Image (cartoon, coloured by chain):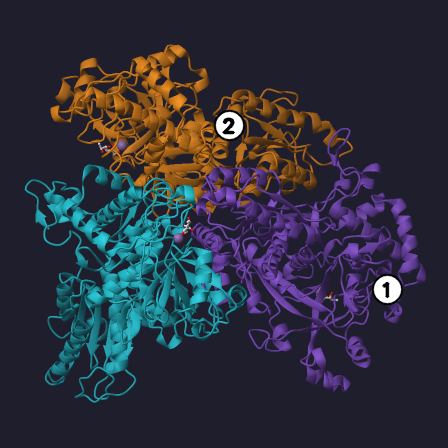
Chain colours: A purple, B cyan, C orange
Amino acid sequence: HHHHHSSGLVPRGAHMAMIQHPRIGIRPTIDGRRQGVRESLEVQTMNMAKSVADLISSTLKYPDGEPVECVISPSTIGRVPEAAASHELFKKSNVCATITVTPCWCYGSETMDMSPDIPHAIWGFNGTERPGAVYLAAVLASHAQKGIPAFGIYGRDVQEASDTDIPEDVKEKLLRYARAALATGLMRDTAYLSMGSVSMGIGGSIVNPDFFQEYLGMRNESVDMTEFTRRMDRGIYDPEEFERALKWVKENVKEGFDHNREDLVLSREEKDRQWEFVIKMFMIGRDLMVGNPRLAELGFEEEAVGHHALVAGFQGQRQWTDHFPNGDFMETFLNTQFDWNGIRKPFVFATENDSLNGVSMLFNYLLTNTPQIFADVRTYWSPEAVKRVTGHTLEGRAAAGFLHLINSGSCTLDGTGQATRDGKPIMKPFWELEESEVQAMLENTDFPPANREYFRGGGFSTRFLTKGDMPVTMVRLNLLKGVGPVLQIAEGYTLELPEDVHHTLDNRTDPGWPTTWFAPRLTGKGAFKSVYDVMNNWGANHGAITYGHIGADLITLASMLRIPVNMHNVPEEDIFRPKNWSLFGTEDLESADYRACQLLGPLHK
Amino acid sequence: HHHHHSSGLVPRGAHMAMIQHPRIGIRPTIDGRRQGVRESLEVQTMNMAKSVADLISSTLKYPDGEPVECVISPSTIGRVPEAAASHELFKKSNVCATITVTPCWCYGSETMDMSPDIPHAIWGFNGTERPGAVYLAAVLASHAQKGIPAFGIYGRDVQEASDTDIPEDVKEKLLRYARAALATGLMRDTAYLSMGSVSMGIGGSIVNPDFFQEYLGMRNESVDMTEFTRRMDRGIYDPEEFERALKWVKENVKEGFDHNREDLVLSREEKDRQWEFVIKMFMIGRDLMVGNPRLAELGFEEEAVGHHALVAGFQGQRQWTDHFPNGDFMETFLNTQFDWNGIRKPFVFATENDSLNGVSMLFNYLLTNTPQIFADVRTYWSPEAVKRVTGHTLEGRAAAGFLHLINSGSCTLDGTGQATRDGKPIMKPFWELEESEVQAMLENTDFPPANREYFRGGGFSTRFLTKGDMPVTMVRLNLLKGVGPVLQIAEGYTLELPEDVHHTLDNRTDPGWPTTWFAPRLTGKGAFKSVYDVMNNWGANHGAITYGHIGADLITLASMLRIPVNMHNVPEEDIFRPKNWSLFGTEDLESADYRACQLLGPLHK
Amino acid sequence: IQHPRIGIRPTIDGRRQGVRESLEVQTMNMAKSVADLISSTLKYPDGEPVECVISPSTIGRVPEAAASHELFKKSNVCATITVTPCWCYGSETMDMSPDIPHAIWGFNGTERPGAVYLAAVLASHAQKGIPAFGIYGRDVQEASDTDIPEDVKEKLLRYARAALATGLMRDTAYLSMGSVSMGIGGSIVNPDFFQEYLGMRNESVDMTEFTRRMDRGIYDPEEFERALKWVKENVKEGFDHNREDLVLSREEKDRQWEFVIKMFMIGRDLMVGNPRLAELGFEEEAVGHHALVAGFQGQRQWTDHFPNGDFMETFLNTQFDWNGIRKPFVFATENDSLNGVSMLFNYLLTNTPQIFADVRTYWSPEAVKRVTGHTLEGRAAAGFLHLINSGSCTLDGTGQATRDGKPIMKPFWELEESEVQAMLENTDFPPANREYFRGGGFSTRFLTKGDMPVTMVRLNLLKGVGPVLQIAEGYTLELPEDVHHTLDNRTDPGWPTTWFAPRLTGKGAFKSVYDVMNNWGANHGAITYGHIGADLITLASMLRIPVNMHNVPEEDIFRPKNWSLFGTEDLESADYRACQLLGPLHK
Ligand SMILES: C[C@H](O)[C@@H](O)[C@@H](O)[C@H](O)CO
Ligand SMILES: C[C@H](O)[C@@H](O)[C@@H](O)[C@H](O)CO
Ligand SMILES: C[C@H](O)[C@@H](O)[C@@H](O)[C@H](O)CO
Ligand SMILES: [Mn+2]
Ligand SMILES: [Mn+2]
Ligand SMILES: [Mn+2]
């Protein structure tokens, strides 16, 4: 951001849209009594605060790889004017959530944080010498009596007064809380950009701004896809960048086998022209999302600013893709953690402008800092169907059947699963990626010409096979009329089928697109009695798939946003929600969660 | 109550506040058809009524030890004008709830009680000769169709027509119903008195009159604590009583070891002055609650009347206890079933003006006629922490860990557990206490000087150890914003630790205060999967602890008041709620209970 | 005293190569004029000029909106004003903050569609449920014109004063001393109301704290000596109406004077803290309770025993004492917290101290005739109300301060020495009536000068709905001297009097002066210098408190623009519907 010689802002340096740095505000509360008690507790109390700040700052990173930032109250908090001084610092410090720490008794409502629009957690030391726990429960009761949600963090094992380690059980809670709170703080005040609008009558592509505004704190931008054509015809993109990209693409991107029907096959001259075009789609999509200071230099100052988009979508079908090369290459590379410019954070991006899938990916992204697989839930494969079709009897993780996850053209190349840790397939934050790993991803992917019976305009799709045995979580938000957003979660594993089984199933389906074979973990409960039941209960044709088991993190996140969780396979002992959820019931956690979300409602209504 | 020579009422005889005598109204309904049927059923029907009245009156007592009173309709009820005559009698008879009894078919809505503001139960004889059961179900359907809650009492085993025993299964239901209904009738129209107001920002001490008014039928009174000072300086207490108390206290109350820091230790002259002062606090607190006719004789006629308080609280901290001796001695003796004047009903009394703990104690008190332990839930002791700290491996009832229950100074001396039945520790109604038992309680208690780093004004705390192996129920009401009161219940046992374990844990905590070691019964369900989970779900720093397993009684009570139960460990087969609860669902009893309480709402809104 | 800012957001057409660069200067000028108008005209309770912030650039596209929001977030902005002369891209340029008021001023000129933006962006505000005021001038202005027209200033300043009132309340506390006073409803303090509507916290101390600080020297002894001396010189003890055997000796009266001074000191220390207390070694007591407003329960338990609260209540609400001229500390008798908030509304809108009073009597013209022989004329002609607190009232409520030979109440920084003198000279302090206040003390007795324009205000809690506001603009009265003395002597001549006549309109509860009283929702009112009804209405609408009753002319009613979508005919109902649906700010 510098000021334009006459009018607006323009970017200089990095993009216009930076990743934000929300802080966590740490509030050490103390007994108010002086002439002995308070003075004797100051040091133990303020240390608790310092140790929490070091835990978070030394463990968690923002999407840009920087260490998360913490702020401590200007003093310990024993009486209201100390709370007010705290609140005043936090207001100007960009604080997205609060952690109160204490080893002693403090005065409930005199010391509590009143912010209704952010999460709070309280950690009471489990010690005998002072009532730390007792404050914990007291102040949480005030929170529930005043309808300001707060998390309760209480360690299992009595600690000695002089001990300053944070117990593993407390750490787990502190970090789950922090990861989830940071996701809320990173979404807030950003936008979703629609390119186009509704795609083929798909629910999530009918974008609902009330949801963004009320639940997420987010704005909605839109451009009609004509914008791409305008920029291409008028030279509103970086031509020097274009030349380097064309060269890198020629070197690194293998064009794939052409399955097109005979009379639909394009000339090699046409295919080359289409390659230039999709490279420009990428640059333009990326520029629209985040801005580009080069656009300003080329004298396109209005365009240089972008659309402040933390997440975005491309309608494509039907009107664009009937005419012009499709968006597979754009969608692929936006979601991939590199291009000709180098290794890079991803730009979270929805196929078919499925805004709800976009937000599902963004939850996943902000919780993990890892890129996100976008997929159609194409087929449920029962053991019986697999046996009939291939002769093979499924075993290990595939034994109970599995789901074919395969988007209609595009997918993050990180979703190959070629990055490695300890001999195992994973998806990594961009700053952990090695050159070899990028190379492996490119090497194990190719780019078949688009199927022109569906995508007359042409383009190239993305084709790889996700490596088996990677822990993942599939995720989907859906909008329920009269209720709002509801969240479903399925943790499980990618699979490696026998090769013949893979090729047989693949070739009957859509072998020009990207494949992940998915087995969800069954629990014998709810919708996880069988793999079939998991599909039959999946509430949209799309899912968002992340590396890792992040179910418990999502559940915590959803409660912060007051989004009820309709379906998950997370063990119950991992469910971690504000302490007042339990006033809405302890047996029927699902109903209590609906009652709590219903009553408190979204953050920004 | 006599009229003053010029103006008000004043008490004479007992106190101004008597314990009330709510009645149970018994309604025998009969088939309307004469010329045979009705006349042949009169005697069997009216006997059912008489036997129910004898059951209740011969088994249950009011808090003052008098036998509960019943009223029968002026005739059997076969047609509406007989129902009207019944309703007319009950209106002037102080009837707090209804029991309809019948051996035959009667005409539904023609015969039913329409009172919306009181509980109803219906007992249909399980006989073959007439449709008793059939009336039972019919009239209950009318109750649910008209939104007037009623309990259904149906015996398991077909009885012979000539049999007049009440089956054990029916008796259990009749008496649970009656105990709970009487508690509602005893609370109604009484008050809660606040002395002071908010204590150290504690939730329950921010008194919510909507709750008292709407749910309990109760008023709220308040005095600023200055009132104590006024009465002490102006001689507004009984000086003859004061002298007898001072003497009894010198003989019966052992002053305890002084743990104070050296420069804070008070002179013996000061300690003696403080003893006089806390004796006066007691008398004044007791007088404020219930009135005193002696105050009238001494010419303080306004004060003699009291505050009509069935339950009350003393703020204490911070402003009073920073200056004057604290309220431990007052709170202790109000909750204890004796003093210098003799053996006595308790006066239900909250530390720190925790009005919600007060009501929790009062539920417990009205259900049992036994005094009530007020406690901080200070510490969860895991087996691992106990092993580390003491070397001991916990066994029997303590094996899964336990809770340290220990109020910040005061507790009913009945909570020593020194009263005995059949070789076992219990807490008794006052009229069952023996002189030896009072003596045991005094003998096993002492009264340490208050800790002046917390209670600068001084005073004496109460110190004993509750005997192990007593069945108890811990209880807490909490206010949930947008919902109202919700009730949690944990039945279990007091523990006897090995002596070394006890002293080690005690001495690290607050050995000048009273201790109960508590193990809740685990069920493998909800919040009772582990002792840790029970604490982690306890919704305030306070609990109310009663002798006995009274979970099922509380659940019945809560349904009468439409307070949902968020957490309990009572077996499901014991849950006994109005029959329409089951129209709100039969599987998810917790959700159905929230839906039912939500829809019907409190009694007096 | 916080310094909440107003954020000025200059929005602009995003199209360059001409349009945008041509409008930059004129657009930025609108921002600058508004900042100047506000900063040169309004002041915080402490006398300092109000502060504004402008967006770091004009706003034509969303990332500029984002930057504006980033800056305002750290600049303590309590409300926004968008200004524009041109068309701009509605939802791309709008402020989304749900917890603060907004206003849009669109230039009324022809060359560019500024009124078009104004209405389009307000449509978005209504459709997204984020209330915003619309500010549109009556007369087409020339593109180069730089004057803010008078209709526009009036709206901008009304908006700003009301916005600032919300900004100054937020995050402060109400302190109760004691609890419930004599079963008075407003003294059963409701924290949900404070928390949800006002963004305020609740603090609490038992009156025992007073005794504690007195016994233990927890107040400033230098200050005490200077105060005792100043009070002997300046404060006139009044007539003792007590019956013979209740009359106190001169010694006892003198000890009580020392005590009530100490009460004043402790009350003030409790509200705002005092660094002298830390110097004297009570570091805890030194910080105070962060109270923008407070009350003192008093009766029954304290005033039965100890000197009453009148002196403390009077001087907290007065703009001076032995330490010099000074802002008031808004303070409620009987801990009537609703009256306290009513006073504070008036205070924050005007920077002038506030009369607390019981609405004691309605005097009909018939009854004045019967009792006095006199036939009321002038403003008094249609009857009137006796406003008189049970012992205390701000000395500024004498009406001794003067502007243009007319009685007023002034912000403290406009007070002259001679005016303080006049307030003192026209007040005496009668011993407390010991049948009602056994514990003693001294009340405050004066008579408010007549012909002073005032507004009486009351906030009431209505079960299941929440707070509702009632407003009566009117005038103080001067009665014939002998008529005054007859009415006074048979009521409570030891307490302070204001004679009030509300303006009648023949609408609603303002058809007669009796109707005004018959519809008054409590025994208390807060009374301010000035006719500020229109300001209250705007403030009420900011906080979503319905107005149940007011005598303000309909043309002056200025509410967020989406109120009109709830109805244009039946404004009262539309107001209730809007507040009901929108709810308090901090639910
Ligand atoms: C080719 C088809 O139109 C395909 O694009 C759709 O089924 C789409 O994937 C649905 O999300
Ligand atoms: C000594 C402490 O203030 C103690 O009184 C508190 O923790 C209190 O027991 C909380 O209920
Ligand atoms: C003397 C009375 O108590 C008086 O104080 C009451 O009328 C009080 O003014 C009610 O506001
Ligand atoms: Mn699809
Ligand atoms: Mn306690
Ligand atoms: Mn009054």
How many residues crowd mark 2 within 10 Å: few (<14), some (14–19), many (20+)? many
Which label sits on residue C155?
Answer: 2
Furthest toward the left, the residue is B5
Task: Give the image quarter of residue C411.
Answer: top left
What amino acid is found at the position of numbered circle 2 in the picture?
Answer: Lys
Q: Residues within 10 Å of mark 1 (few under 14, many from 20)?
A: some
The answer as to whether the residues below labels 2 and 1 share one chain is no
Q: Note whether A198 is above or below C289 in the view shown.
A: below
Front residue of this view, candidates C403 and C266: C266
Point out the frontmost of discs 2 and 1: 1
Label 2, secondary structure: give it: helix
A252 left or right, relative to A603: right
Q: Quadrant of residue C209?
A: top left
Helix, strand or loop under label 1: helix
Picture coordinates of residue A551, whole percent (x, y): 62, 64
Identify the residue position indicated by label 1 in the image: A440
Report the front residue among C548 and C135.
Answer: C548
Position in image of residue C61 (x %, y %) = 69, 39
- Residue B119: in sight, yes or no? no
